[PDB]
Length: 138
Length: 138
Length: 138
Ligand SMILES: [Mg+2]
Ligand SMILES: [Mg+2]
Ligand SMILES: [Mg+2]
Image (cartoon, rainbow over all chains, first blue to last red; front, side):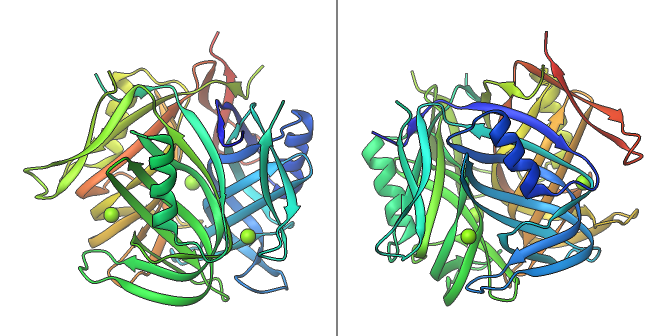
C-alpha cells in the first residue's frame, strides 16, 4: 500500500547563476530519489520562468525576486513544482515552475524523500494528463 | 511534554471534482491522525473558497487556479488551513481556507503526522477563540 | 558529509502580541537547535516587517493580516526566513522577514530539526554575503 513512509531529509544550497530545474534534477539523480518533495525553501532569483494557470506558454521574467515558496513533488523522471516570487514592491507572482529560473544570491532547500514509496507519473483518464501515482518502494 | 516528535508521512493525490476540505477530513479519519500538518502541496482548483483576513464572510470564486501553497494543521476534529492560489495572469489571492475548494486536474499532498503528540482546539482567554493545544499522545 | 539527516519535529503556538523573530530565536535557544527549518506555519499578524527584494530598508506595516507562508532555515546564531501575508481583500505581500512581526490571534508552527547536520552562515565569495553552510553534527 502507498501513502505511509518515514522521511529522510537533505539540506542544500544552490549558487548564484545556477538554474533551479537542472540543479534539482541533478540532486535527484545523485541521490536516486524516488519519492521526494520540497519541505522547505528560501532564496532569491534573477530570471524566473512560470507557466500561469491554464496557460500553455511559459512566461519569462528577469529582475530582482525573492523566492517566497517553492512547493511540489519530484523524483527520478518527473516532478510537479509551483513557485511564488515577490518583487521590490512586495508584489507576488505565482505559477507552475518551468526550466529557466536562475539563482540570484542563493537558494536554500530542505528536500524530503520517502524511502517506503515510489512516485511515478501515470496517465489519468479523468484529467487527461499524466498524474502522480504512489506505490510501494518494495 | 509537547512539541517534540518524529513524523510519519503520507502521500496522496486528489481527483478532479473532489472538494478539498472533505477529502482531507476523510483522510484524517481513515488514518485516525491526531497531530498532522500539510508538509507539501501542489495542484489546481476550479472553485475556491477563502475567508480573507479579519472577515466573517466566505468569498467564493470560480475559474482556473493553481495552488501555490496550502499550509496548516489538521487532526481528528479540527484544523486551521490557509490557501494561496494564482490565476492565469500570475496574480495571487490568499486567505483562510473554507469548505468549497474543488480540484481541477489534481491536488498532490504530503501530510505529516506527529505520533508522539495530539492536537486539539481549546479556548484561549487571550484571543477569545479556540486555539491550537499540543499535548502528549500518551 | 552533509545534506542527509532524519528529522525531529516540534509543534508550537505563539500568543497574541508576541513578536515572531524573538519567539523563534527563544525556541531555538531553548532546544539548542543547530539545523532547523519551518516545516509548516499558519496564523495571523497585526504588525508586519518585511524587506522587499533587493531593498535595504525594512517596510513596516500594521493592520489585519493572515500568514500564508513562512519559510526558511534557522539555527542557534542565524536564520533566513521569508514571509507572505494576505490582507482583508485577499491581496498578498511577500519579502524577507525582519524583526517586528507581531502575532494577532495566533501563530501555529511545525519546526523541523536535522540532528545529523549543523547549519552556519559563512561568507560566500560568489554572492558577497554570508550564506548557508551545511556540515555534519559530529
Ligand atoms: Mg502544476
Ligand atoms: Mg486562519
Ligand atoms: Mg532572503
